[PDB]
Image (tube, rainbow over all chains, first blue to last red; front, side, top):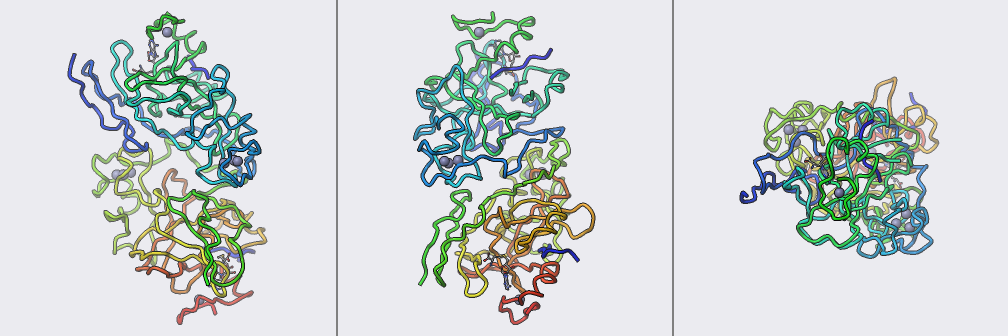
Length: 7
Length: 9
Length: 258
Length: 261
Ligand SMILES: Nc1ncnc2c1ncn2[C@@H]1O[C@H](CSCC[C@H](N)C(=O)O)[C@@H](O)[C@H]1O
Ligand SMILES: Nc1ncnc2c1ncn2[C@@H]1O[C@H](CSCC[C@H](N)C(=O)O)[C@@H](O)[C@H]1O
Ligand SMILES: [Zn+2]
Ligand SMILES: [Zn+2]
Ligand SMILES: [Zn+2]
Ligand SMILES: [Zn+2]
Ligand SMILES: [Zn+2]
Ligand SMILES: [Zn+2]
Ligand SMILES: [Zn+2]
Ligand SMILES: [Zn+2]
């Protein structure tokens, strides 16, 4: 439920 | 002692 | 607007091989200092990365590691770096491979072909104040396609810990573990999202080969002209959360999150 | 006649090359170990690298004032403006040195950063007449200069006690209990080749840089006097070495004041 950047 | 030689500071 | 003000000569305090100045030609916002600049990843609670030197795969090359017999090139599918340390044109920027650079167990020299990300940031970058996006990062020079630009550096944390961090703006999933650049970060924490990005993140292994902990290296996807803002695609895992708060302002005519 | 048998034993990992020469016999450059420029582990050592565990300074200058926390931990900052130990430094009984680190507020070029900048001196691996390989300096080294670090595989006291080859073991602490050792037998840098001398021109100093886990000091050799171009490097390996080795061979350092021959 947090924003994570993705590779 | 210890079994092996050690350098020490 | 104001004459451009130099607000720091080097946000890295001399930790990179060139300075990264911060300028503001927009408002009176000071050099951002809500974090500690670190040039390489750190931990708080232990991650237990496997650093057993005997666990490294390595090469026995007697040349500069440009031949197809290089084990480390084989682990990477092939060595993707040209003579200038740029990714070959055939590198798949849509679905990048894992890159395994040479390491201290290899027989080859420290200057072999398969060593680019481990040499650190080289390009002249600048933190600057954007009009409508807070802080951003620009290149001061032309950067040719396929060039290593910078690594996403920060605090390595577990998935669970990332889920309880109050601030999620600086989280990057590894692929699980994360890098949080909120408290500890380098220049990359300031790079904004762009829907047509000039940077692609690639997973890279260097001093260790613990596959839980790839390092995140940004390469240029095209010629980036001097002055241009750096941008990468932050991804769905980001925009699914942040979209409910604000919309993408990258201004691309092919934008996907406004 | 002298042959250069390697232009650089470090394969480019140091700031300058460390050539190997042989003016004695037909041995090639030694190759039965892996050169590494910084410490490694096999079995995990679990060095505490929690960044919030570091003690650090808040200096607004170049860390040359007596307010610098890192100097305070060191008792005082011992480095002059050229990075050499002050004449007041106790070479008979060195204090622990805490250099500045990535948590400090200071810049990367502050006064209190020397060993972390790595090997600078022009050194040479060479074949001695009767002690195997040795290390010499190719240039004058003023007193109090950082020469090189004793680098190798970090292992427990327990594991060290069963290593059959004990010519390259260096104890990090002289106490009982939980203690660790550097073994430079299988992985090491140029320091592994330094011979014992009874009147040494190097002294080992315990140093902390990126972490301050007191179980794992790093071992930095400083010059105890001017070392002239051409002189062999030597340090006192100590009683815990010669108590074992002296039953096997005597010291050949050649000092008129030799204590182990
Ligand atoms: N394409 C985009 N559109 C709108 N806001 C963006 C954006 N890319 C980044 N941001 C803003 O910047 C945050 C990511 S951190 C990037 C640095 C930030 N601009 C700063 O001033 O520190 C996002 O949560 C959002 O607030
Ligand atoms: N003062 C001394 N007298 C005799 N032998 C010594 C010595 N100092 C070092 N050595 C030799 O070197 C070993 C330490 S390792 C130092 C490098 C070694 N000469 C080499 O050729 O690899 C010792 O155990 C001993 O074998
Ligand atoms: Zn190779
Ligand atoms: Zn390799
Ligand atoms: Zn290589
Ligand atoms: Zn967009
Ligand atoms: Zn200080
Ligand atoms: Zn400090
Ligand atoms: Zn300092
Ligand atoms: Zn002697």
